[PDB]
Image (tube, rainbow, N blue to C red):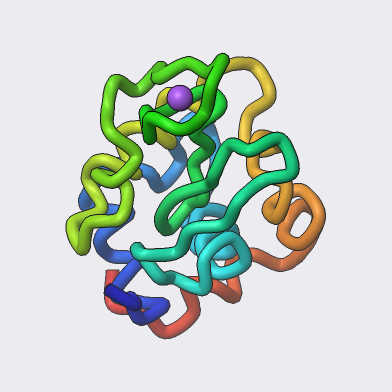
Length: 129
Ligand code: NA
């Protein structure tokens, strides 16, 4: 599923991300925009052989099991395929664990390089939230 911008904002809100570890909703939207273009089916292979999955490009090196990332963890205890669902609960729940682990949203390289230090409130302009 390819979410609309406001549609995604409202689902992320409902799922408890706005101000999660202090990151406002527009941070999470901006990150989803640049990580996946708001597409829950987005996958991209990393150089190391791990793969990033879903709307927030969660990595099989640490967070989920895809059975082809040798020498990896599954810290969210989920198959990576659960991260591709049109229902974003699994992605959200896992993103909570990632953002809590010490580096905040710097864990998302697109957030750091494309959202951090920018006007992210724009990402939620005109959404009925
Ligand atoms: Na893994």
